[PDB]
Length: 227
Length: 225
Ligand SMILES: [Ca+2]
Ligand SMILES: [Ca+2]
Image: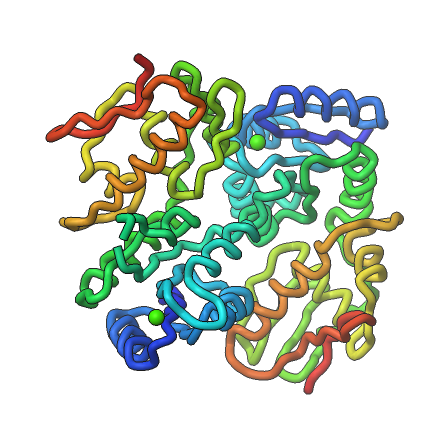
């Protein structure tokens, strides 16, 4: 009953993923390149999209870029070959919500797709008032972050992360807690998605040129706090 | 401003490159050896790296090797020497080179070219291109000859990919410099001819037929026969 659009230009992989997800309980639509992805996404509006990065015609990065420019927040998990790192990172930066490296076992994708759906248009936060951490203001309801009055341009998943960290300002959250609260994971994962997104957030928070607000507590977790 | 990391163990040269590139409109990071180069590259994600070859602690060839081994496709222009007539940094995976001594205008032109290429979002509609025994998987950035992987550096593939996309077309040195290297300017560099050599040698390793042809005074063509 959730509709998942799966996009890959490798016809074996696409057929396999189609088979795998349909059997796992999803209504599945497919596309072979990013143009067909955007057509499919536009004409059918999937609940989630599984999106290969390196494709002809329009790549996965472009597809993501395009969706997000249209304010289309559909959850997206990008797929990439192992070696195609600085590149899957591009999809995440451009606005994908999660990634999975090939080859993967099908359970890894199903689990992340159910998480994607659990956390589509998101946060597990109750704050209504804007949250201040030094010069940073995190407006959860208005989905707006500002540092010294200047908006910080964040993707939907960067913002969800910052929002969870602001909701628990000054508290340390572990990778595992952040996978559950932000990504909606209900399973143990081998993933550095939290680390990658902490990198992006911190770079954005610091681009102005002042204090580190977002701290890595080695072996324990991450914390948003002034000083 | 594009961020360029410059790496040279000679502090005079390092300082001079830094000054020059900054006055040319670049945001410049520096590193004194290959170890500092790796740290800077990780901590600071430069848009391009100007990389000396002979350095203590860790050399330019080792830097390029480590970067490529770690799937970091950052543009690298190596500052290298030229005997063997080999340019070891290129073979290791650097994208272009300059031979010291050089004028700054040559480095600036080459760094802009690096950046032009890395900045390109042009996406081909081609999938796998077949030329006789050779298959070029464009989107997958893989080549195989008679089903056997040909291990190519990023820039070797870039060149192979342009030749395959225009398969059987003769592309001049000038067009490949523009198309593959991102040059917008004159350049008397031999970099295209050097990489053609690399590809031939790699493509022809399995004993097979010549697929990459040099038409002197005209250009280069990838075709079976
Ligand atoms: Ca692909
Ligand atoms: Ca040196």
